[PDB]
Length: 143
Length: 140
Image 1 (cartoon, helix red, strand yellow):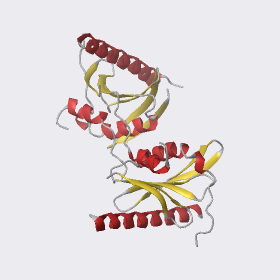
Image 2 (cartoon, rainbow over the protein chains, first blue to last red):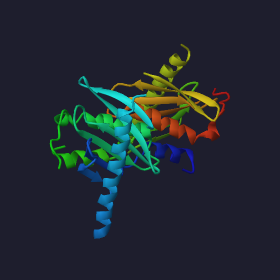
Image 3 (cartoon, rainbow over the protein chains, first blue to last red):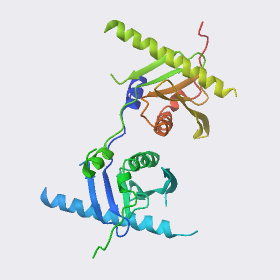
Image 4 (cartoon, helix red, strand yellow):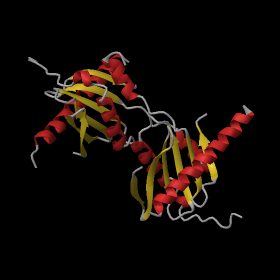
């Protein structure tokens, strides 16, 4: 902004979109469903790159879960269901991931480096409350 | 939403605008500058109502200062406190511009998460270094 009015007008404006949003498997990081806010071979590359991010974040999630002794970790409760929200730097992108409570599924948000980690934590907690149908969801055999 | 793709598409979307944003005096809560996110007598009414909210929030801020959560923050060795207050249905966030006689004030709908107000107001405050230590003189 170039002046006070303009500064304030800018403070009114919403923060931008997430880059992508996913439900992925907690077991192998496979994508079950996804949305992006975004020619043919570009689309494929694009899905492959999503598959790679989901895998890496699941791997970091998994490491932190089993590490007895991570950008940050926030325990949350939803109707006496517990889960943990994690944030991760991913090559200049900001990511946020949480296990859907008692389930084999993770919810994953990916955003630009300017999107504040704190807002990801808030959004993912609010979103997780909409996914009660998926609480307890169990995958069976995958191969 | 109605299905999983729809739910995920919704999670992509930005949060809405603030209802309003302003710089007001820490002394009396008078408005110096403001912006809102959207007849004659409606426009005047609308300004009167902002004046009234600014006054009330300044009064609450004043109380808390000489004694609804509070987050201390630092911007290059300068300190200030971020406060959130429920209005009626509205969510509000106010912080003194460091070392100054000014407050920065955000007002949002009841659905706007307090935590985001706290985040936004700290980010916005960082663009306001020009106004650090600004002093009001006589206001007659």
